[PDB]
Length: 424
Length: 65
Image (cartoon, rainbow over all chains, first blue to last red):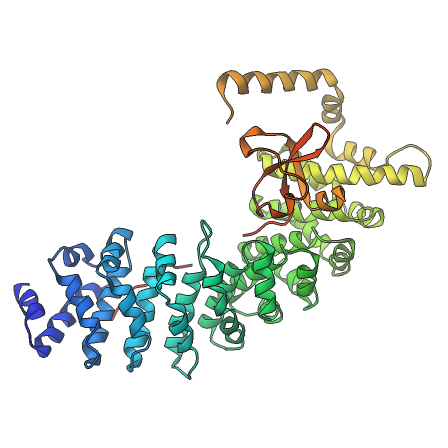
């Protein structure tokens, strides 16, 4: 409308508000709103950014903030104009506004801008969003504020390529720790998502996360009723146990394994997979830690999963079994063999995925090596797991691989095609 | 020494030149979780490895009436 444009650029606060309110309602109507039609109008987005500065009018500041938030949702191209209009620095000022409504919609706006990409996330961090954002948590705010603030926080910590500079996001760790004591499912879920991102990386980042005290509460949230909390809690836990052996003991001490054994029976397939994945990171542990998994009765369930679950779950359980065989003692491997791990591992050798075959081959290799230890404990010179692998895999297939002439043929065929046709 | 480090690494095969020059056993602890790299395991023996320990919602929201 031309009265929308007139009233917007006019100099009366009544008409300014009235026009802006009609602008919001068009971007609030639910079917993917007309963002570009608004953004293309000359000086209109910059006019909304000018309204954010008007500290003596709560309603107008909120309506403006609501509008720019919704423009900020959607395309990167659309979210570009909001940044270039210079709204980020001003939204961060509004985090210290005297009106709650304004403070809270500023956070949401910035959450959207932080969520657009790696480069927008860092700019927001480089405009010092964090100090005022963490100050929101410093008072008894309403529940919707707390949710919006943690959600924004999680968007600041998010992204792997490249991740945020750790010194800019790690100060939020103290807040995240006490937020795991809140009951609200939305806040718990996003607090966990934030932590899963912060512990995704080298072991110095995991040390900062453990140092904040979060592992016990994380481990406790693996038993929540809502998969919205369990998924991210499980993702954080799984990442922390990609730590050295000290770091992963920190989680075992919180009794994670009985909770992990429970999540292996989950009806939700992605939780099953994530629980295998987590457990495989622990079985990459020391023999002590492999024994704790044995004593929790985890392996019968992993072996069941290894032979009946869908591929992507099967692959994680394979990693779990194989890491156990890389690190474990002869007696621990003997037990895994007695629960029947060789057959499922052999069955993976025929699957058309080179990554799972690598893992399966590595586990069979480790089993066989320890079978040489048992072939000198008993003095026969017979590896006991030779006959078992033969039973599982087939004499045909063993005979094919026993041929050095077959080995020479494949080596040459691979070498030849890769050289003249290129590798792929 | 060597096998105390390599314990935590799955050996994938021999040197694969497209993953860069070979690392030492000491550089190996800085290899990113999930990435692959060549290491000198000894003499002229270069091998491709990865770590056994492996790392892992709505990005934006619109306000409506």
